[PDB]
Length: 297
Image (cartoon, rainbow, N blue to C red; front, side):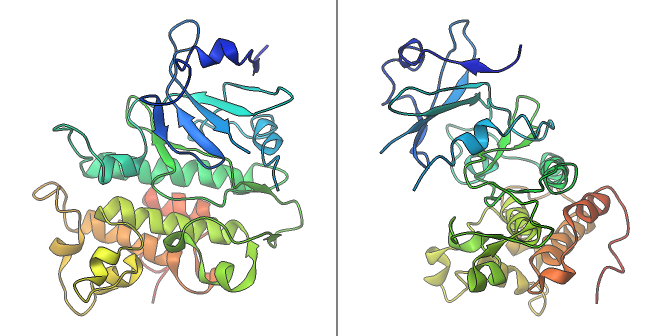
């Protein structure tokens, strides 16, 4: 067919009585666990722990949303008790994981990998908002949330804050959750999410992916610069200097104008008025070479 009920225990054991050295992070309603299906497949299984059912809404997710820059749920578990979600294990983890927390002597993303994460993700995002009916609001775009396959392809993942609209185009009226540096001002101001807040989010991800930085650092604050990753970059303008903002670990390894364009973009996307942010798809065009230079003033 193509969608998998599991017999839990049969998965306890695929995660070795779960916890411990199985944790790929203390997840959002519990925890992401590493995992070898019965065959020897790798799955990141999500666990539930003690409102709710924003479950079912990502079970019924695939049956409305398949694109290959969107993580795809293998299967699930019901039981009278707890609830879990199997996604394909992503060999190379989040873009974040690749940027802060890179193990041994593990190598960091070079430009074009960065280039490719930018487009593919803009890509699945553009699908969600456009070629789905009801529209789909992701509500959680951040590097942490962009996964990477074996050939370092961006997969927008974690559908656990994800809301179907319909409700024409404007907004889904829903309680402001996520972390700080990823929330659109009006979202914050106003309770409502929306394709235009996914943008914002998305554009801040670019800045991550561009920078190394977290969207909101206290470390920065300890140096009289801005805790606000946006605001930092915009010390871009005056202090005319690329070099410092751009992720240290790329040195001779990008070219000046490649990076300008991509910044121009996150900037077009994080603008204050929703109205002027590119639609995710105009975002894709622009990544694909299509008409940025006027889209601004």
